[PDB]
Length: 492
Ligand SMILES: NC(=O)c1ccc[n+]([C@@H]2O[C@H](COP(=O)([O-])OP(=O)(O)OC[C@H]3O[C@@H](n4cnc5c(N)ncnc54)[C@H](O)[C@@H]3O)[C@@H](O)[C@H]2O)c1
Image (cartoon, rainbow, N blue to C red; front, side, top):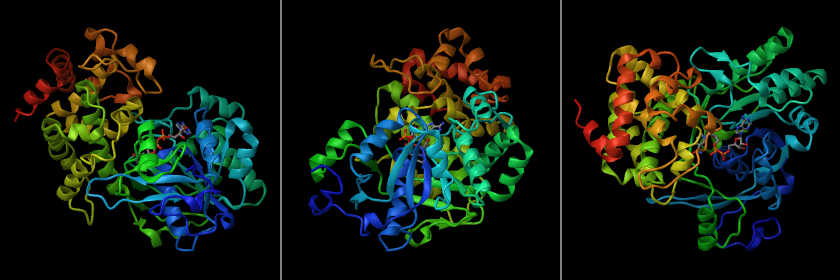
């Protein structure tokens, strides 16, 4: 049965349906970057609130700034913006639920002004983001906003026909001001240690390139809450979509699949209101940064440590690496010896138990999370997930070998062929550029480690780290992933 409003009451019995009248919802959030995570997390909690009969005025209007967003818009529009949330887990108490909290999705390609108008409408009180780890344009080595990027220069030159998130948000805020409409809160839901602070720094830096006045007004009227957002959400591959039809009879052009576990801890900093998400499990705390630092360092850091080595070994899913005891031992050593000592205190959390839950969640066999997804965009993910840890090891004079292996694994992985002879394309926005850095084995450490917006300035200037990187890369190439891990796991 095709998922749409017409068929909503004719799906399998076990399928949970929105308990509110879809036609009575009104928009309050504009979400930029409608992919899987937004749908499995923010749209999920908002739909859960609506099912209690509250917050029906907090519907989401999706926003797509990229050509690839057209397919998402068309797939959802063909379902009256309904989509299936399909939870997959082993120690499972999982549900299949139709989500009705997204009511539309606008594309910049259809009209820049229609999108500005939507973002500037008084009903829209929060502009949320899942624009990916590298979408904020801040160079982590020096904390500088990357004003020179072409799309940023484009928006400065054509503020009324922007293409980036910064250009759209500034144009919307200017229009709201001219109408006497209050600012909205900008709510980042991306994996950055201090995601709200980064969003603030970037938007202000961009606004400053326009005029001090817009910059000053934004600094004083817009809030940028930090958050820890957590819910493993694989890509919806054909197999995931077919499994939904096979098991629950729904023909959904684009369901979202995700693990049963879900958490959201937010700083309560909203200038123009927000849904009562705490009624459905969202947690609010004064300073969420140590929790987000913790999750990024341990969960995302471990994901990168597993993913390139796993792809090279020939694995294709996260649970497969967890079925390899050498990978599990390596992740535990990385988490316990390299990351843990660097973490700020996390009130109410026992780190040992938390690290075990990461092992448990990554071991979920039913979810089938793709290493191709986890590997994607390493050029933007390294400075967020791994380099901070490496820099601390370098500064402390601590062993860098396990962390260096992650970077060496990525370097070898960029050549595009695994140990079984299977060739792959590199899913990275700077793929061509990164593959170029590894065209000559003898020059890899000099070229790859010298990209400042990826690795910073400590790594290339560290003899200890460079030697470890070179040892690791040669071992991976000559002896393979398995033998390299065995040797490493025996170092003191
Ligand atoms: N997938 C997960 O398990 C998970 C968990 C926690 C947080 N996240 C966060 O959410 C993000 C998106 O993950 P996803 O799985 O939904 O990915 P996805 O590939 O399904 O969607 C990414 C979305 O971002 C848009 N996008 C990319 N670059 C952009 C840019 N510069 N400006 C505006 N939009 C841009 C894409 O067009 C698309 O709509 C991650 O990068 C991460 O920060 C994901």
